[PDB]
Structures are given as C-alpha cells and as structure tokens.
C-alpha cells in the first residue's frame, strides 16, 4: 500500500516518477574530464613509512587508470543512453580529445564545438596531473626517493580518492551509472552545468532546487582515456 515508492522524494520536495519521465523530451550531454599524469613505476631507495604510503597511493592511481583503460575498450538507437553513447563515439575521433584539452587549459569550463556538429559543454573537474607533476614528480623521479612530509600523503589521498571512487562506480556498473553520484559530478559542478544549459531560467530553478532528483534522472557514461585525459559523458534530462 506504500505508494511513496512511485515518487521521487527529497527532504523538501517530492515528484511522481512516471510524471517526470513522461515530461522528458530530450537529453543534454556534457563531457566531464579529469587531467591525468602519465607516469611509469619509478623504483628508488624507499625505506621510511612516508615513501611507502605515497607509492601505495601511487599504485592505486596506476591501477585505477589501467582499470578504466580496460573499461573504455570494453562496454544503440533505442538505448536510454544512446545520446551519451553517440557523443562518446565523437570523442574517439582522433583530434577531439586535444580540442577539449586545449579549451580547458585556462578554465575548468568551456563550450567546445566537436567535429560532428554538436556543441558540447566540457568540464575539467579534477586536475591530477598538475598535482602529481608538481608535488610528486620532483620527489620520486630521482635516483633516491625524496621524503614527502606526512601531510603531503594526506593531501594526495584526498585528491586521488575521487578518481578511485569514480573507477569503482564505473567498474561495478560496467561503465554506465545512475544515479549520478557526487564523485562523478559534485553539487557545485552539477549546478554550474544546469546554469549553462540551453533551457529557461525557470527550468534552471526547477533543476537547481531538485538536484538530487536530477541525479536519479541522469546517467554517467565512461567514454575514453586518451592523452592524459579521462573523459566521461553525463547525460541529463531535457523537459521542453
């Protein structure tokens, strides 16, 4: 007799699931990118605890990258994610990934015209290469490993945690996840994407007020790792 299961429910709002799904008229696809460091396993004189912890965190960084590389090689028309899948194909066209990277070199957001006709908003939500190439490359790219003070270990785990969780969600879901978690797209990132969507301001108010409901109506789709860029497509509903 519990009719609540037929309703999206948040702390302040509820929406009928069938009514919301029926109102959908299209999909909006965005490209979410994480900048990665292409670093091989460097072996040097590692004795103390802090070096072990960094290399253990580094190993998990390497495993997550290789796991996602196996996903992109792994993984139409009538599918619920056919919109996002089509965008992934364009990203596989040689030259698109560098185009997205060039536009995100100075900002974490930029509108990019692909080489199929679609203009797609692109985000860079995490810059791991910048952190690794400036805080860890000087320490470990040596004959004898440098000593990273224990707070550097904590910082790197903080930043690396998001990549591991994203890899974990993609691995157990075979590359397609719903609802879109806060690790795929934080609330701040999701609200920013909504504000730049080609919809009305009232629609932006509707989605911004109900971010949790938007997550349950959206998909996150793994696309590619290429040229130090991890790219996945977030597919958001359009009610127009």
Image: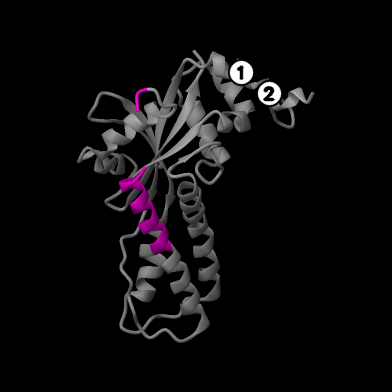
Rendered position, 127 above or below 89: below
Q: How crowded is mark 1: few (under 14 residues within 10 Å), some or many (20 or more)?
A: few
Q: How many marks?
A: 2
- Residue 47 in percent (x, y) is at 45, 87
Q: Where is residue 225 in the image (x, y as percent from the top left)?
A: 32, 49
- Magenta span dominant secondary structure: helix
- Write down the region rendered in magenta: 61-77
SS label for mark 1: helix
161 left or right, relative to 69: right
For mark 2, give the secondary structure: helix
Q: Identify the residue at image location x=42%, y=68%.
A: 59
Residue 104 at what x, y percent from top left? 34, 42
Q: In the orientation shown, which residue stands out farthest toward the left? A: 94
Residue at 56%, 33% (x, y): give it: 215
Label 1 sits on residue: 18
Name the residue rendered at 74%, 25% in the picture. 4
Label 1 with label 2: CB-CB less than 8 Å? yes
Q: Residues within 10 Å of mark 2 (few under 14, many from 20)?
A: few
Residue 6 is marked as 2
Give me the residue at 62% from left, 33% from top. 212
């Amino acid at each position: 007799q519990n009719i609540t299961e037929e309703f999206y429910q948040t702390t302040a709002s509820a929406v009928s699931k069938g009514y919301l799904s029926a109102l959908r008229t299209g999909w909006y696809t965005s490209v979410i990118t994480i900048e990665l460091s292409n670093i091989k396993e460097n072996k040097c004189n590692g004795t103390d605890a802090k070096v072990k912890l960094i290399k253990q965190e580094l190993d998990k960084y390497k495993n997550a990258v290789t796991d996602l590389q196996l996903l992109m090689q792994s993984t139409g028309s009538g599918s619920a994610i056919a919109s996002g899948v089509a965008v992934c194909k364009v990203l596989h066209l040689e030259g698109e990934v560098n185009k997205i990277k060039s536009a995100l070199l100075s900002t974490n957001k930029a509108v990019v015209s692909l080489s199929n006709g679609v203009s797609v908003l692109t985000f860079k939500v995490l810059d791991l290469k910048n952190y690794i190439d400036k805080q860890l490359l000087p320490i470990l790219n040596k004959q004898s490993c440098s000593i990273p003070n224990i707070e550097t270990v904590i910082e790197f785990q903080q930043k690396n945690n998001r990549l591991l969780e994203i890899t974990r969600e993609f691995s157990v879901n075979a590359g397609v996840t719903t609802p879109v978690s806060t690790y795929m797209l934080t609330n701040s990132e999701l609200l920013s994407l909504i504000n730049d969507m080609p919809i009305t301001n009232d629609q932006k108010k509707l989605m911004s007020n109900n971010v949790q409901i938007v997550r349950q109506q959206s998909y996150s789709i793994m696309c590619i790792i290429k040229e130090e860029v991890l790219a996945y497509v977030v597919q958001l509903p359009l009610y127009g």
